[PDB]
Image (tube, rainbow, N blue to C red):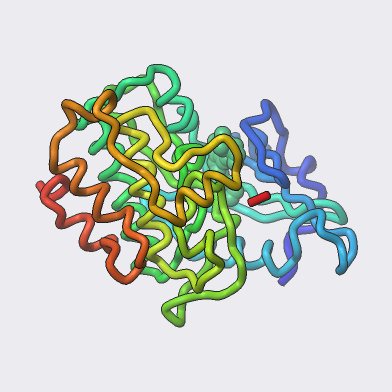
Length: 278
Ligand SMILES: OC[C@@H]1O[C@@H](n2cnc3c(NCCc4ccccc4)ncnc32)[C@H](O)[C@@H]1O
């Protein structure tokens, strides 16, 4: 499939840089005809078929196809797609309040209620996606954006569908691999992947929200991945001594090696704590 090949600068002005991937840079922009503001993700194309730099057209088209399906308050919308010889440019919904990651850094101590307020929204967004058989496969605090950081209960949106796949056959097998601290054991072990991997990532995110510490993190990526595969984490009393047993129960039921035994998205919403590479 082909995208709009007019110069994006004919239709938009760009501003500040909002962030980046390998890979990809995201800039604020403004549509000339409406005055509305967006975020534009510039993804570098592969320059040859044999090249390992840039993103393959297959991978770009998959991301665009998935994004076109989605509309839910807790997920980003896609507005337009442009392309030229070097880039595909995905224009989508600006989320102005920064990363949950940055958030957590400033300040860094969340109550269980602040943590569950974030979590409930993440779970609602993932419920929507999983209902559509979409695995995100890159859930982490860098990919959860706040609409407005200056309100007591910030609203969030899930972003970055660069690794997202449709799961039409219960699992997919193609060596998808995100950030070591957040990937499930099946990703580490190059096993077939399904919606369960996202549920593991949610358990990791929850642990971080409550404690400010990363449960599997080692001194090298190697060591992190080995920790993940062995399910080598524990609840440090220094961080968790006054966290409720139910919060710990929730995380325990997500950080499970066997994906078949791990809580599903529907399970997570009914759980008593929630229910009202190289
Ligand atoms: O991805 C690196 C990042 O750069 C920033 N970022 C990425 N997407 C952002 C956005 N909106 C998405 C609009 C979009 C929708 C659909 C396709 C492409 C982009 N709003 C604000 N900051 C964003 C964050 O700091 C991230 O950690």
